[PDB]
Image (cartoon, coloured by chain):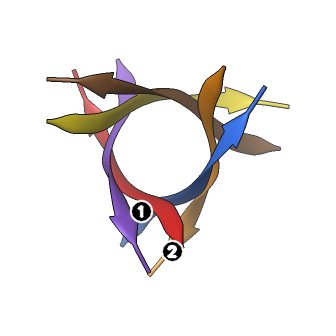
Chain colours: A orange, B brown, C yellow, D purple, E red, F blue
Amino acid sequence: KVKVLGDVIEV
Amino acid sequence: KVKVLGDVIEV
Amino acid sequence: KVKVLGDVIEV
Amino acid sequence: KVKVLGDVIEV
Amino acid sequence: KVKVLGDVIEV
Amino acid sequence: KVKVLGDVIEV
């Protein structure tokens, strides 16, 4: 299954 | 730790 | 259209 | 409620 | 490369 | 600014 994994970042 | 988990959807 | 929908989680 | 909304991009 | 870019929103 | 950066993965 395709999923999204990521991070909360400051830009 | 804070992370992001989600899905790819069609809208 | 393809979009991403997800959640902020604690791991 | 906090949620994540985003896009699939090419980089 | 495919990546995800998005926002933290209130719903 | 807070943003989300992530990856499309297979699980």
Residue at image x 83%, y 44%? B1
Looking at the rendered structure, the kind of residue marked 1 is Lys
| Residue A3 sits in quarter | top right
| Residue receiving disc 1 | F3
Q: How far apart are marks 1 and 2 (CA)?
A: 6 Å
B4, C10: nearer the viewer: B4
Q: How many callouts does the rendering have?
A: 2
In the displayed structure, does residue B11 sit left or right of residue F3? left
Residue at image x 56%, y 67%? A9
In the displayed structure, does residue C11 sit left or right of residue E2? right
Answer few, some or many: residues within 10 Å of disc 2's Cα (few below 14, many 20 plus, some between 14 and 19).
few
Q: Is mark 1 on a helix, strand or loop?
A: strand
- The image shows residue B6, relative to residue D5, as above or below, that is above
Position of the C terminus of chain E, as image quadrant, is: top left
Asked whether the residues under the numbered discs 1 and 2 touch, taking CB atoms below 8 Å apart as contact, a structural biologist would say yes
Looking at the rendered structure, the kind of residue marked 2 is Glu
Answer few, some or many: residues within 10 Å of disc 1's Cα (few below 14, many 20 plus, some between 14 and 19).
some
- The image shows residue B6, relative to residue B2, as above or below, that is above
In the displayed structure, does residue E9 sit left or right of residue E5? left
| Residue F7 sits in quarter | bottom right
The circle drawn on residue A10 is: 2
Position of the N terminus of chain E, as image quadrant, is: bottom right
